[PDB]
Amino acid sequence: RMVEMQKDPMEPPRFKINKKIPRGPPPAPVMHMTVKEQ
Amino acid sequence: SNIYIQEPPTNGKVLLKTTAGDIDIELWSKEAPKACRNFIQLCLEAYYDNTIFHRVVPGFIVQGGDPTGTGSGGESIYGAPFKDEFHSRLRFNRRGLVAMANAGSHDNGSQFFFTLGRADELNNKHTIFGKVTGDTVYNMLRLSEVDIDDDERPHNPHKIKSCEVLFNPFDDIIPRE
Amino acid sequence: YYRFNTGPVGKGPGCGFWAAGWRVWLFFMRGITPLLERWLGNLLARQFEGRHSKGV
Amino acid sequence: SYQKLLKYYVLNALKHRPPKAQKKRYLFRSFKATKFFQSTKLDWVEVGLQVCRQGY
Amino acid sequence: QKEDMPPEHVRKIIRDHGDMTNRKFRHDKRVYLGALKYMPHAVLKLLENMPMPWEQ
Amino acid sequence: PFDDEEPPLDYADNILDVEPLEAIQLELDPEEDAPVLDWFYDHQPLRDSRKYVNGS
Ligand SMILES: O=P(O)(O)O[C@H]1[C@H](OP(=O)(O)O)[C@@H](OP(=O)(O)O)[C@H](OP(=O)(O)O)[C@@H](OP(=O)(O)O)[C@H]1OP(=O)(O)O
């Protein structure tokens, strides 16, 4: 029998979220010079 | 134009006639009915007559109330050491306080002591049943002027010659014979 | 005070008749309450959750 | 002072939008229905003392 | 219904916890702090129920 | 009314025991003011009366 635990309404945010971790990394294929121009 | 001093109003008054002069004690019988009942009845019973002050610690306390004068004696009106009574409004911030000596909790005897100064370490330990009135204060302090011999005992200890109860807050006190 | 101290009664200290003043602070409190809930809420949340890192 | 009280009077009357939108949310009923709060009855004075201690 | 309790219960709780400086109390320190958010609410309800000068 | 270093009072230790000391009141005429006179200075005058008010 699952029961949801009662939360104390005057309880502050329990734990700290601020921590920051670098953005995660397949490329679709692209399918898309003269000397003088260079 | 305000200088505040907070303390609950007292009730009852008792006169102690000592070799050091008169001492007026205003009692709190609302806060400490047990020890003030004990004190009033023991005064009415002549139990404190010719009882010395056997312990003087310079600038700390002067102790008396033992009929035997040894300091380990004395008994209450209740046939046993009675309970301690404490209040946040009664503290030791000063000399001029009249409190109950004990060897521990609920140990209260007939022995009592006057505060020669501040004791913050006796808080929530000894019960405060009274205070000495300013006019008579110096006389209390003369109780503390002695040449002190071994084990905090004066060579010529001051005595309580008699007792007068000036105002008795209790209706029902019957002195024992 | 003007109306109260009308006749024999002088400029002296003793006039009780608060009801009015009392009202005023209650109106104040009615409004300020939600403000303080929101501000103190944030204060607590910063205290416990942490000042947000990103300044996003 | 009489002039200023009229100014408050009139401004309130001018300003008087209806609520304009309404919610019947209840706070003490939510708090009271939850086990962390209990209810009783005390001397007002006694509560006042309790609140000051709590705030301290 | 949340039947009300003996008044001495709340009296004693606060008196026990009077300063939540006791080593034993610990976890109230976090809980108590959390409430601060609703303290102004409490104040407003306190004040609006003052007793009037004809009531003892 | 009290010093900063003076801690707040336990209601139960001082206040609870003590009398309430007379309120302001007024000397209503037994004759002329009789209708009003029995309940005039009670807290919520006619709370228990199915004649005068709705009810609780
Ligand atoms: O007569 P009182 O009962 O002592 O009232 C005085 C006084 O009122 P009146 O002078 O009108 O009689 C002050 O007036 P002023 O001295 O400033 O002319 C007034 O001052 P305000 O004009 O700022 O109200 C002052 O209050 P305060 O002493 O803060 O200035 C207030 O007495 P309270 O201080 O008792 O209000």
Image (cartoon, rainbow, N blue to C red):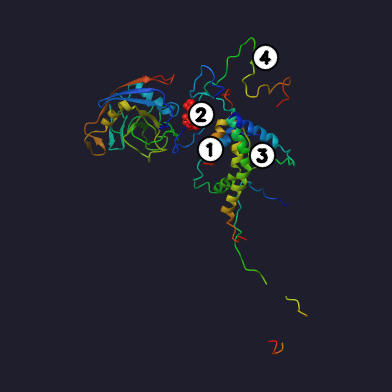
> Disc 3 residue type?
Phe
Chain of residue at mark 1: D
Q: Is residue F26 left or right of residue B49?
A: right
**C6 in relation to F5, above or below:** above
Q: Residue at x 29, y 38 (%)?
A: B59
> Disc 4 residue type?
Pro
- Spatial distance from mark 4 to mark 1, Cα to Cα? 41 Å
Can you tell which mark lies on residue F15?
Answer: 2
Do pointers 4 and 3 mark residues of a single chain? no
- Under tag 1, what secondary structure? helix
- Spatial distance from mark 4 to mark 3, Cα to Cα? 38 Å
Chain of residue at mark 4: F
Screen quadrant of the N terminus of chain D:
top right
- Spatial distance from mark 4 to mark 2, Cα to Cα? 35 Å
> Disc 1 residue type?
Cys
- Of residue D28 and residue A18, the one placed in the foreground of this image is A18
User: In the current view of this chain or complex, which residue is farthest to the top?
Assistant: F31
**A37 in relation to A29, above or below:** below
- What crowding class fits label 1: few (fewer than 14 Cα within 10 Å), some (14-19), or many (20 or more)? few
Residue pointed to by mark 3: D28
